[PDB]
Image 1 (cartoon, rainbow, N blue to C red):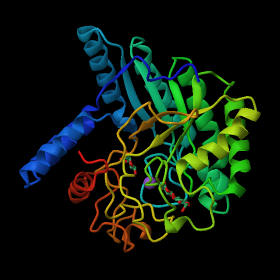
Image 2: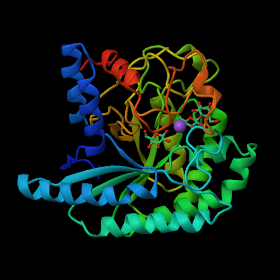
Image 3: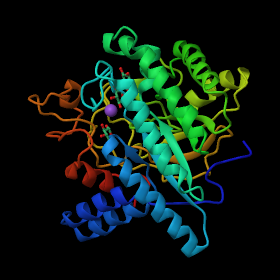
Image 4: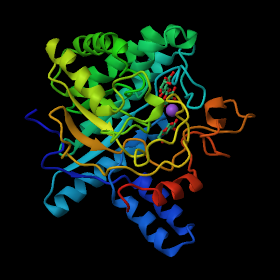
Length: 358
Ligand SMILES: OC[C@H]1O[C@@H](O[C@H]2[C@H](O)[C@@H](O)[C@@H](O)O[C@@H]2CO)[C@H](O)[C@@H](O)[C@@H]1O
Ligand SMILES: OC[C@H]1O[C@@H](O)[C@H](O)[C@@H](O)[C@@H]1O
Ligand code: NA
């Protein structure tokens, strides 16, 4: 549409990821690969607010972006992910979080949003783009038979609504998470998904700051596949552009001129999974298309890197309380540490297998 949030802005590079990358490049023995690994810190990524402990860090990022803009005569943009719902990750085990519905989860989540809003309010010269709660809404479309998800439904919707309503008041551009082609792209799931997204958008007042949806977050699908990956058999929507082209018209019909952003951070290498539902630390993944607003689709505002490559998806250690057997499958890189922590050997392969090369 007419207002692409990235036009005319310089993206503030994540200091969190830059520090991880700088440390990781020092441990890569090949000198040519080390130099290429270090340059990853100059590629824009989303910074995840996966715990209330990281809200003070958001404040420092905003202040630093503000100063950088004034220094260089540019307008700066900070990219964040809101990811702290109570009973988070309801259909899996690896990314269970700090809040629970049973122990004042919604109240705690509302306080988490309020503290984020309080930081953003102090730096109105910095634009913020937020991805809202990966996996949450997609789980309420296909996983209501999962008891943890069914019991979380009303809390999820209330929390997401609280996030959308209050971040809109400080002018944050928001993309709700919308799974990926292998999850909601199945033709039979498109209409239920559209009805849920539309209902969420209506409940939050149809604010123009709710730009649309994010797809493929933390996953590996192609935006435009040369030929279908074999795991996609049975689904005509075998890549993200197929999914988006089928879903976007249903949202427009409901009055929402919705646009999309698509994660390609780990999509450089296709045809590496045994089943489409294998999501954890997939072996042989490579960095994908670099972020750009030259997307080739009327519906896509930007290709982005939301999940930061090198940060683990979950542990292969069967003794951990967060052990998910998806992370022990033959196509999952092992041994792997806890979700969110650095996975050096995985980062090194992402660099080596990057397509296009670094
Ligand atoms: O995409 C990353 C998330 O995947 C979630 O699992 C999905 C999977 O992606 C789909 O392909 C299909 O198998 O449904 C699964 C959900 O039941 C996973 O639960 C999340 O933790 C990942 O972030
Ligand atoms: O790497 C980005 C995010 O990935 C998720 O799987 C983890 O649970 C988070 O802790 C992390 O912030
Ligand atoms: Na995950």
